Amino acid sequence: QTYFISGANRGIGFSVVQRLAAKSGVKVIATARDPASATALNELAKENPQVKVVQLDISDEESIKKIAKNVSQYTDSIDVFVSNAAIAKSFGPLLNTPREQWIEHFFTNVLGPIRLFQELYPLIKKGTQKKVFFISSNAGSLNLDFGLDFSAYGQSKAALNYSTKELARQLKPENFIVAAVHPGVVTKITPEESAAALCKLFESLNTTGKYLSYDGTELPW
Amino acid sequence: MEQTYFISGANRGIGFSVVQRLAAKSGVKVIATARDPASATALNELAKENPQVKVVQLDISDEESIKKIAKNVSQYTDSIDVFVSNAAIAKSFGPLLNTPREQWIEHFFTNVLGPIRLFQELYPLIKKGTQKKVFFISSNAGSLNLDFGLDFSAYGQSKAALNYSTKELARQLKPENFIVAAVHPGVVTKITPEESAAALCKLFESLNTTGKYLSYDGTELPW
Ligand SMILES: NC(=O)c1ccc[n+]([C@@H]2O[C@H](COP(=O)([O-])OP(=O)(O)OC[C@H]3O[C@@H](n4cnc5c(N)ncnc54)[C@H](OP(=O)(O)O)[C@@H]3O)[C@@H](O)[C@H]2O)c1
Ligand SMILES: NC(=O)c1ccc[n+]([C@@H]2O[C@H](COP(=O)([O-])OP(=O)(O)OC[C@H]3O[C@@H](n4cnc5c(N)ncnc54)[C@H](OP(=O)(O)O)[C@@H]3O)[C@@H](O)[C@H]2O)c1
Image (cartoon, rainbow over the protein chains, first blue to last red):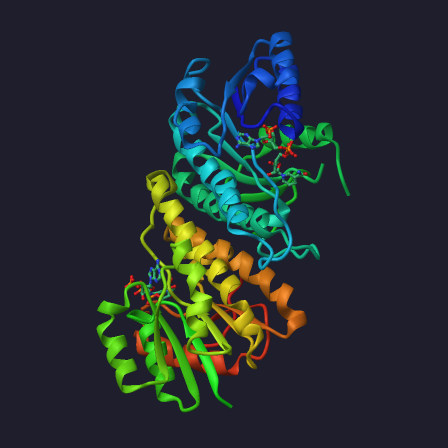
């Protein structure tokens, strides 16, 4: 089984790769914007050479345009795709959210993952599990009220949630498993706990179209 | 008792029919926008016969047009009672894998950021008026909880994104006694733009509560 994780240099992403590397016969394609500076990740892959460290900046169309070749070097197929790399920089009122915050969350948090998936679909198609995971947020629900505004961040997660739902429909007749997943907040949980829950969720999940919290319970779109 | 309405995209479709419906009411000034007024024949003829109809250039895809809308609307009115973000595109349907980069971008810029920026620019005029009504023309296709079997690609994504932000805005501006709504105007079983316009103008006048996702008939849609 070949897993792919965007944004593995730190946070939940690093914690997922670290758990995958422990598991028998898991090859992990793990990305960073700057793999040369990804001290902890590189260290992981030297210690566990089944972990391959590829360059990806999801905000950069020219970086996304190489991801298939870069991943093609290490695998003929992806079993489980995880769009984890994402930003979360702007919150609060719309009147107080400038143009740039909106644009950046769009390109990085919505277009990024759609292009990433578009590029890597041929490699996912050739694989066995045909599992596609977009790491969303519960803040992306149209039907949850946190007593908070999420500005471009929330909008971005809602937009990707919309397209995830659509993708789940479109790829059902190819036995694909597409899910949006809230990894928790890191009541706060450790990267290690988030990772553990997600790895369990990645192997267990058998139906497509779901919007799941890390614990495996459903969220309202 | 004089009310100013603002409609983005009034040169054709639902936009024109709304301006036309409004022009018939007495004590209603209408700020009607067109990307290219020079060639807005029907809308210019409406304004020529109806001096209460003011035509103004707006491209919601163009930050340079948005920077100008406040000062330019301000030549024609001191306030906006009812804001209607009607101008949109619908140029992307079908599967995610067949939707090229450019259709995602264009739908974001025109259908999400355009209206946000337009509202930002026009908020102070709307703060200054009586009705404080803020309508975003959405689609039932933007619902995260309706299934029509069809793919709406970047169009639907753009309507969901604006929906999410519309709902947050209804929260933010409840303390300033704003009425904020996303409205599905119908599919134009089809209705005509004139029926859509008659039902929308009824809704604009009657809606007395914020934070709704509505169809043209005043029934609620799930987010
Ligand atoms: N934070 C939460 O608790 C929470 C809650 C709900 C959902 N989520 C989702 O879970 C994901 C993982 O969160 P995290 O907490 O691990 O985030 P993080 O550590 O704060 O940073 C996000 C990760 O993505 C990478 N990244 C950022 N921009 C990138 C770009 N343009 N191209 C490629 N990679 C980029 C980052 O690398 P750099 O180090 O280079 O920035 C980092 O690995 C989030 O991105 C978010 O959407 C998180
Ligand atoms: N038609 C339907 O069945 C339907 C269904 C659901 C929702 N809606 C929504 O209802 C609203 C009205 O649509 P419609 O049916 O009247 O369709 P339409 O004919 O496409 O309406 C477009 C209007 O918006 C203007 N516009 C387009 N792009 C613009 C831009 N970049 N800047 C400024 N103005 C621009 C158009 O002007 P130009 O002449 O310059 O293009 C035109 O006046 C739209 O927001 C649409 O999304 C319509």
